[PDB]
Image 1 (cartoon, chains in turn yellow, brown):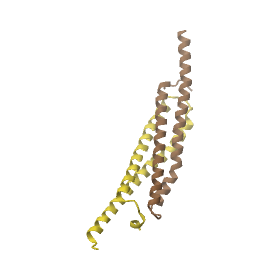
Image 2: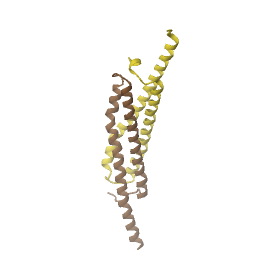
Image 3: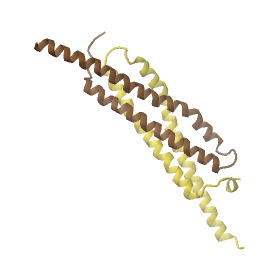
Image 4: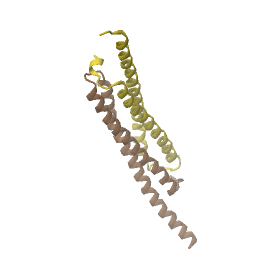
Length: 98
Length: 97
């Protein structure tokens, strides 16, 4: 099971996790910023010139939100797994006598 | 249809900069974490992480498309700013001359 299958240490799992949460946050910020820019362009440039970019942005936008959410979910899984593994090491050290 | 475009060339260019910067940032995150997904895959035997792998893989091409869209918007904003800037110059010269 996992104790056999996982080769990353708790520390390695935590270092990987940090990359995912930082990327989640960065993606969210980009999307939030450019959502505002899209609205500014829409309001301050009358007509249909950017209608196709508007539709494409709006179609992709929820995928970007999902991606940010996925990256954060992965951070949480890796942190939780790291804690379970670290406690396993401690429990073997305390409970096993060999 | 009004002809008026309320954003000035300078304003259009400031917005374009945000699109291309955002594009780069999204691509960097996808690059870094594509590589980290392969680390996890190689260092976690079996199928336990398979769903997170599938979820990442399904979204990845959309992320690449998004980053390209952002670059495309940048490019067209710069093009429109240049058209407007010439027009502004031609009107200013016409009125002053």
